[PDB]
Amino acid sequence: DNPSLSIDLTFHLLRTLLELARTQSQRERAEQNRIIFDSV
């Protein structure tokens, strides 16, 4: 079957690209909240 050698790294690295963005967003939404709150 497919060893997914190139997929593992890609699927792993691509995961980080979104995982990091999602996590960042997670705080972003809260940060932007205070950022905007203190600058409405």
Image: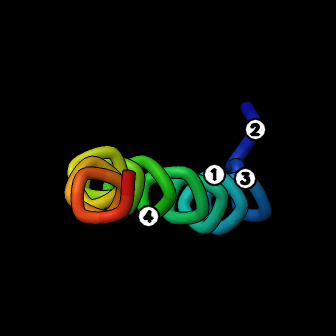
What residue would you read off at disc 2? 2
The span from disc 4 to disc 3 (Cα, nearest Å) is 19 Å
Q: CA distance from mark 1 to mark 4?
A: 14 Å
| Label 3 or label 2, whichever comes before in sequence order | 2
Q: Residues within 10 Å of mark 2 (few under 14, many from 20)?
A: few
Dot 3 crowding, Cα within 10 Å, few <14, some 14–19, many 20+:
few
Marks 2/4: CA distance? 28 Å
Mark 4 sits on what residue?
20
Front position in the image: 18 or 24: 24
Judge by depth and name the residue closer to the eye, 10 or 40.
Answer: 40
- Residue beneath the point at 21% across and 49% down: 30
- Residue located at (69% from left, 49% from top): 3
Looking at the rendered image, the disc whose residue lies closer to the viewer, 3 or 2, is 3
Q: Which residue is mark 1?
A: 11
Name which of mark 4 and mark 3 comes first in the sequence: 3
Q: Which residue is farthest front? A: 40
**Labels 1, 4: front one:** 4
Number of the label disc, if any, that sits on residue 7: 3
Spatial separation of the CA atoms under disc 3 and disc 1: 5 Å
For the residues labelled 3 and 1, say whether their Cβ atoms are less than 8 Å apart: yes
Q: Mark 2 and mark 3 in contact (Cβ < 8 Å)?
A: yes
State whether residue 9 is above or below residue 23: below
* Element on which disc 4 rests: helix
From the top left corner, tell me how far across and down residue 9 is, in percent.
Answer: 64, 68
Position above or below: 27 against 1: below
Q: Which kind of residue does numbered mark 1 sit on?
A: Phe
* C-alpha distance separating marks 2 and 1: 14 Å
For label 1, count other residues whose C-alpha is less than 10 Å away and answer few (under 14), some (14-19) or many (20+).
few
Q: Which mark sits nearer the N-terminus, 1 or 4? A: 1
Asked which secondary structure carries label 2, the reply is: loop
